[PDB]
Image 1 (cartoon, protein in one colour):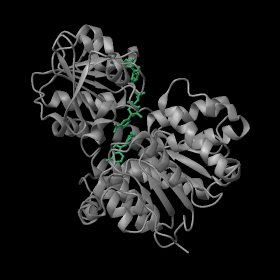
Image 2 (cartoon, helix red, strand yellow; image 1 turned 45 degrees about the horizontal axis):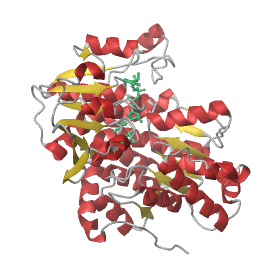
Image 3 (cartoon, helix red, strand yellow; image 1 turned 180 degrees about the vertical axis):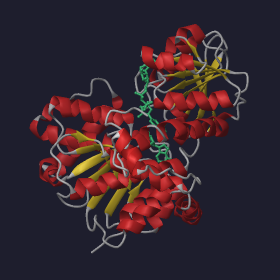
Amino acid sequence: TTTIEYQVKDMSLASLGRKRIEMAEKEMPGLMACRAKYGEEKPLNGVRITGSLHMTVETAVLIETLKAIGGNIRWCSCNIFSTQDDAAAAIAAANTPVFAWKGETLVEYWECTWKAIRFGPYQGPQLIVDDGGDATLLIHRGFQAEKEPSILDEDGGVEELRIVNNLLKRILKEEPGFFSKIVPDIKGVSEETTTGVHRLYAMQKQGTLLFPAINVNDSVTKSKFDNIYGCRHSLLDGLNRATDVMLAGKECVICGFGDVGKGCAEALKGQGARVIVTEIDPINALQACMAGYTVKTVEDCLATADIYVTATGNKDIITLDHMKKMKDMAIICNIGHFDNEIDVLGLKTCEGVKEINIKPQVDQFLFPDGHSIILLAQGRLVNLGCATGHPAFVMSASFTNQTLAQISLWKDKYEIGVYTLPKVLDEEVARLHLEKLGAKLTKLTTSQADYIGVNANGPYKADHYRY
Ligand SMILES: NC(=O)c1ccc[n+]([C@@H]2O[C@H](COP(=O)([O-])OP(=O)(O)OC[C@H]3O[C@@H](n4cnc5c(N)ncnc54)[C@H](O)[C@@H]3O)[C@@H](O)[C@H]2O)c1
Ligand SMILES: Nc1ncnc2c1ncn2[C@@H]1O[C@H](CO)[C@@H](O)[C@H]1O
């Protein structure tokens, strides 16, 4: 019945990855609580689960939690540089299909996404774990291409869209109507990150969303923990391993002051950096002012700034024109999305600019006047591409949300639309992580609960409370 199938860099790394997974398990009380609560009953028993999410040690604990509660799983990474090859080998060695390695080409990246989606002839996932929406995109675009085949000849100059179109042309030639066949079996997708959730709301607004979606990013125990304190840890780690640069006394520019930018600026400040924030939103800008940061434009900073971190989810933050005017050896990295926050394509196609590799994921771009910039991870996620991403404890919060979302998509009735988990579940995720930290929660008396108008067991806040 069950065939072994995987594609990883180096299976001899499996034992090392398995040791790191065992360490991570002891840092992830929320995921272990999910195994303890659901491991016998197996609410996801036999349910086909496709995952597209950074193949890290932390993700390995999520995969094997979903497996412990019954899932029939296939996995790929959502980023060409974020896979930890030893974690991928350890997952493959424990007989879960995984198609992921550090340093994929874009063609390989999309081929792995397709491998993780296709469970068999005319068979796809019933649940999807997604991070950034690329697996969701492939399914929606393949479905659309059955009705509108001309979109597969339209890339709009974008090389990656050409790659996706070529893949979908081949898929639909091999299995005509594949996506209209498998889409009715998809019970839903749970989406990890701000950018992927933006794609979901856009599809829902246009009425093109094909199945229910849980916005996991906007659990309070995800957005206000992972995005902030995960980055506070892992931006520093990515910069350290890539460059070993001392931050103290350096002028560091954080582009964007949402949840990611807030955690990045706090990390930099704690290491003695002079932190500058850029923002388009006057509210987030005023928050940066109240925290003691200087709020400027990128243009204002070019003559003096030492390091640039893009954290916007937007494009064209750091342009070729900017980089021409930067100080020599300025470090440029992206912790937001994709690879277009920095104009890497412009760097690579500007005839006078010479690219010189320093070490893996660290590249010098030398300009005719003799100054250079240092680009990290080809402009992709620096925390995951140059280091190991967020640490396990905070990913346990994000991934406990993922696990509860998966169970809910399977067990509960959803209409097509985008949903968030109930506040009582959000509160439960937080509860599951308090004991490990030694925190002791206060219990309301009956009189106190009446006075503020809540059930003593929650939820404790109005639905639009912002924390
Ligand atoms: N690397 C990681 O581990 C990690 C973790 C969580 C989220 N993310 C990603 O980080 C990105 C940001 O996430 P978030 O949750 O902070 O989103 P967010 O919406 O809360 O914050 C982004 C901010 O960027 C600002 N911004 C937009 N365009 C700008 C521009 N041109 N110049 C300056 N500022 C601009 C917006 O005003 C906004 O406040 C997303 O792509 C998200 O998916 C990455
Ligand atoms: N070690 C990590 N393992 C898995 N996912 C991570 C890790 N660090 C950050 N991420 C996720 O990557 C997303 C961005 O693609 C963030 O929303 C975050 O949840």
